[PDB]
RNA sequence: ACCCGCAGAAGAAGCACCGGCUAACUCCGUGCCAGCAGCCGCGGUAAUACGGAGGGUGCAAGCGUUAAUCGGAAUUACUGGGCGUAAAGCGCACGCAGGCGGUUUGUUAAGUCAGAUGUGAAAUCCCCGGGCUCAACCUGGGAACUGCAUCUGAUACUGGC
RNA sequence: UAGCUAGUAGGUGGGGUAACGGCUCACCUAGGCGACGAUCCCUAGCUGGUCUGAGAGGAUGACCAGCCACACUGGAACUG
């Protein structure tokens, strides 16, 4: 019922990709419960483009929320 | 937008120099200022208070070539942080790239400087520029591209820049043809004839 | 000067509504010609003013002015109108405009052509 | 350091035997750019001579005030008939603001920023002479020390 | 403490209801004066200690009838 | 004027100095003598005298020094019907900061200078220049 | 996406306006006619307003033009008005609810203000960054959103006893 | 717009429901509301907000945020 998922942002052609905890109900980008990081595609050519709150994520998935396999693969990019 | 009359027609209607159609003659010749005043102003009109006002508003605009919708935007930006529209307006015109490329001597006029940007001949901070209506800030570096350094109009503009007072707001080197902005301009350091008495009271009664 | 009276009788204001009410908030309206005529001679201004009566699908019928030099408008012809007062006419607040299937265009016009709509002369 | 300002100038019409006659009238102020201003009205044949008659009235009396930071010592009120004028002191060198029928009376006395407003009827002679009544309403210093401040 | 109100009994004979008036002040949104506002409700009573124009103390309970979701606790003046 | 006796307290003073009088008289009350000490403490008056007990009257002696009047403006803003309330940080600065505002708080009258320091607000009594 | 070149002026300017308000107009055409507007009106043989010639003035891949919503409009006044005569006291006496009410000791604490716990989401207005031709925008942080809901305190004052 | 209800106004026992309720069948009475504007027709979904202005106020909700209603037009049940 609640998933740790992606939110595209940036309207047309200019995505920002935020990672959020959200219900399967209502919104597809906004209306989220808690933000847990970002996956920004244009990060000034620096490694600052990816952030993930692994402690809060572990508590959300522990308590019963779904973690996406796409986000589980991205946990490796913040070490680790 | 353009001006399709002879560019000295403006200065000959004003009875004052506006820095228009400039090159290796520098000043006064064959500007015919007060020698060919035309069909009006000899004989300078009294007219309405709405004269100065409009004809004084045009004289503070056309000297920078700025369009009315730009001029209203600079009046909005000059009305920021209590800086005074009689003062902080000058920084938005004198700090504009088609004035900076002119003050650096790459163009002999603000029109010719604006043309050099529309012809992609200029760089700002190592990247090419095509927009000339843009603000420059301290530590920004402006230069002419090697593919355009040999144009006779730039050659003449640099020889005219040596016949002009040097600005205290920006630097330029004639050997690299590269200049850098240093500080934003001030009324009592610009020390020249430009209005105050109308740019303190625009768009209101 | 008392404090609780406007709870008993709130004070009223005048809304400006319309001087061109048949438009129903549109820049133009289409209708049919019912009559083509000229107005009665009026004021020390001496002229022969061209007018038509126009009927609209919304229950309005209005008199409208026929600008431009010369016209041949028939009755039952479909026409467009635009709002605006003309004081040389009696109570007229509408202009009938030349974009019509039966109506003639203005001729011998080289300048000011964005009004009435005239194409640039050959040679 | 004498300076003069024209605020308004117009023609007038008058009835005579079987017809009318035309003449000129002006509204002016005169000041010293540092503490005083006087107000003038005048009518004449020829427009420069009408303006000059108003300048001579503006020299017939002047009001002398102790300007503070190029603005007002305190808030002031001025009145003439239906024309009521109020002025709040201005901060940060900005705040000007106010039309010529208030501003011209103050820009001739040395005022740089002021938050003046006019109320009621907008006959500019009445507004100008109510601005002068507001200059008779201002007080001097910053000396009596009767208040803690500020 | 529990939710209580005081008021005067407007209507006292309704078998198993009494009608109470509750008074408070509120600001008028345009004319700025704080004006009096009065609200009415039905209150449940089985014990008959009050009468018309007598003063009561009441609590909120469960909805039972049209505008009756409150019940009587005590009488506050009692003399008379 | 008995329907607003504190508006009348200000009226008697505003018209008293317009007539350039030294003394102003009114019927006495605890709030009028609480305000009279605020007016003495700002130096608009040099004395406030109560006579009678037995038709008690309050007589205020105006303090004329260094020129005409004792105040330039003396507005009440509040009214018994239209009561005007300010929060501790919404207290206005009267006379471009050269004047006082007075508030009744929850214990009695004080100036905006003291209401600021105490962290208090309340109903407006006067704005004085 | 982004960036660089090639022979060549190469394919490239129109629209409105010109007495008074509100700047630009001289000379003609017409001659109360024909056609303009926001308003007076412009026009009868020397019409700045209509049409034409040559120019001027403003804007420009636009230019003019308008229904529809606000400001100006204090012209409905809550901020912010008037009632002798311009716009208005309603022909004149009594009077219930409504609304108003001197001065002081208690007391309730609804209202008020204070304090605290929640709220005023994402945006957005304002200041300063990041990133896409400038800027918008999309984004990052501040500052705001002067408000609102409740639980305690104080009772100057309005209500209440 | 000066009339408006009538499961309306106040009680009683079952049945229905996750559960208040005249939800629903019976039975026990006759009121209840309103000029301090009840109530009914005409038009219209509402709001984050947007537009205007110094603000009050005025306008308005597409587009970007959030509910409701609605599924040829009218009507009936199941499933949950």
Image (cartoon, coloured by chain):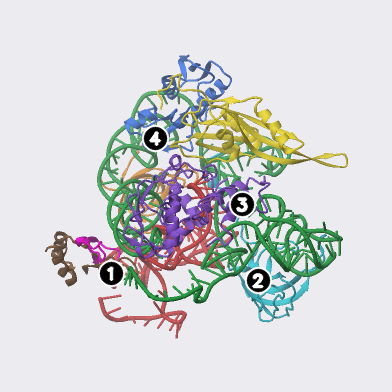
Chain colours: A brown, B purple, C cyan, D yellow, E orange, F blue, G green, H red
Residue G98: percent from the left, percent from the top?
51, 42
Q: Are marks 4 and 3 in contact (CB under 8 Å)?
A: no
According to the image, label 4 marks what residue? F122
Spatial separation of the CA atoms under disc 3 and disc 2: 31 Å
Instruction: Tally the numbered discs.
Output: 4
Residue nearest the viewer, comparing B46 with B176:
B176
According to the image, label 3 marks what residue? B13
- Determine whether the residue tagged by mark 2 lies in a helix, strand or loop: loop
- Residue A25 colored in magenta in the image: yes
According to the image, label 1 marks what residue? A25
According to the image, label 2 marks what residue? C113
Region of the chain picked out in magenta, as a range: A20-48
> Vertical placement of C49 versus F13: above or below?
below
Within 10 Å of the Cα at label 2, are there few (<14), some (14-19), or many (20+) other Cα atoms?
A: few
Residue nearest the viewer, comparing G91 with D80:
D80
In which quadrant of the rendered view does residue D32 lie?
Answer: top right
Looking at this view, name the residue that lies furthest to the right: D18
Q: Quadrant of the N terminus of chain C?
A: top right
> Vertical placement of D113 versus B183: above or below?
above
In which quadrant of the rendered view does residue G40 lie?
Answer: bottom right
């Amino acid at each position: 019922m609640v998933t740790i998922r992606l939110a595209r942002h940036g309207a047309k052609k200019r995505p920002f990709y935020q990672v959020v905890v959200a219900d399967s109900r209502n919104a597809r980008n906004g209306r989220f419960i808690e933000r847990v990081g970002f996956f920004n595609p244009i990060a000034s050519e620096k490694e600052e483009g990816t952030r993930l709150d692994l402690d809060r994520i572990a508590h959300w998935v522990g308590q019963g929320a779904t973690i996406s396999d796409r986000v589980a693969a991205l946990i490796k990019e913040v070490n680790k | 937008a353009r001006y399709l009359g002879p560019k000295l027609k403006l200065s000959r209607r004003e009875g004052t120099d506006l820095f228009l159609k400039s090159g290796v003659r520098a000043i006064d010749t064959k500007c015919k200022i007060e020698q060919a005043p035309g069909q009006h102003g000899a004989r300078k009109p009294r007219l309405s208070d709405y004269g100065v006002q409009l004809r004084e508003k045009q004289k503070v605009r056309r000297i920078y070539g700025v369009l009315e919708r730009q001029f209203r935007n600079y009046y909005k930006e000059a009305a920021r942080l209590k800086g005074n529209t009689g003062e902080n307006l000058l920084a938005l015109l004198e700090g504009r790239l088609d004035n900076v490329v002119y003050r650096m001597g790459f163009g002999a006029t603000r029109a010719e400087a604006r043309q050099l940007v529309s012809h992609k001949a200029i760089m700002v901070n190592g990247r090419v520029v095509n927009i000339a209506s843009y603000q420059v800030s301290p530590n920004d570096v402006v230069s002419i591209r090697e593919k355009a350094k040999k144009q006779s109009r730039v050659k003449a503009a640099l020889e005219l820049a040596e016949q002009r007072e040097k600005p205290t707001w920006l630097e330029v080197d004639a050997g690299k043809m590269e200049g850098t902005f240093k500080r934003k301009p001030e009324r009592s350091d610009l020390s020249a004839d430009i209005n105050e008495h109308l740019i303190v009271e625009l768009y209101s009664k | 000067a008392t404090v609780n009276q406007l709870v008993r009788k709130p004070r009223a204001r005048k809304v400006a509504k319309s001087n061109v009410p048949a438009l129903e908030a549109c820049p133009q309206k289409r209708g049919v010609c019912t009559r083509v005529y000229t107005t009665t001679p009026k004021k020390p201004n001496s002229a022969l003013r061209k007018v038509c009566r126009v009927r609209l699908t919304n229950g309005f019928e209005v008199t409208s002015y026929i600008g431009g030099e010369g016209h041949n408008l028939q009755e039952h012809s479909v026409i467009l109108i635009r709002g605006g007062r003309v004081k040389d006419l009696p109570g007229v607040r509408y202009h009938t405009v030349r974009g019509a299937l039966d109506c003639s265009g203005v001729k011998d016009r080289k300048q000011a052509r964005s009004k009435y709509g005239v194409k640039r002369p050959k040679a | 350091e004498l300076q003069e300002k024209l605020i308004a100038v117009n023609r007038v019409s008058k009835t005579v035997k079987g017809g009318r006659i035309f003449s000129f009238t002006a509204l002016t102020v005169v000041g010293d750019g540092n503490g005083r201003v006087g107000f003038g009205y005048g009518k004449a044949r020829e427009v420069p001579a009408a303006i000059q008659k108003a300048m001579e009235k503006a020299r017939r009396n002047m009001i002398n005030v102790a300007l503070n930071n190029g603005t007002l010592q305190h808030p002031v009120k001025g009145v003439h008939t239906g024309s009521r004028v109020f002025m709040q002191p201005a901060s940060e060198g900005t705040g000007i603001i106010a039309g010529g029928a208030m501003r011209a009376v103050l820009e001739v006395a040395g005022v740089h920023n002021v938050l003046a407003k006019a109320y009621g009827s907008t006959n500019p002679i009445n507004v100008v002479r109510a601005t002068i009544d507001g200059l008779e309403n201002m007080n001097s210093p910053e000396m009596v020390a009767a208040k803690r401040g500020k | 403490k529990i939710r209580t109100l005081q008021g005067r009994v407007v209507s006292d004979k309704m078998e198993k209801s009494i009608v109470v008036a509750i008074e408070r002040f509120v600001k008028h949104p345009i004319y700025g004066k704080f004006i009096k506002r009065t609200t009415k409700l039905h209150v449940h009573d089985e014990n008959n200690e009050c009468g018309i124009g007598d003063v009561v103390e009441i609590r909120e309970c469960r909805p039972l009838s049209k505008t009756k979701s409150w019940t009587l606790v005590r009488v506050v003046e009692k003399a008379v | 004027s008995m329907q607003d006796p504190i508006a009348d307290m200000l009226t008697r003073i505003r018209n008293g100095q317009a007539a350039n009088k030294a003394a102003v008289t009114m019927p006495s009350s605890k709030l009028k003598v609480a305000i009279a000490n605020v007016l003495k403490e700002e130096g608009f008056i040099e004395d406030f005298k109560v006579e009678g007990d037995t038709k008690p009257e309050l007589e205020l002696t105006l303090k004329y020094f260094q020129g005409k009047a004792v105040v330039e403006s003396i507005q009440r803003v509040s009214r018994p019907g239209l009561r005007i309330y300010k929060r501790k940080d919404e207290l206005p600065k009267v006379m471009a900061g050269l004047g006082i505002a007075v508030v009744s708080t929850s214990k009695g009258v004080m100036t905006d200078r003291a209401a600021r320091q105490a962290g208090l607000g309340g109903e407006i009594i006067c704005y004085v220049a």
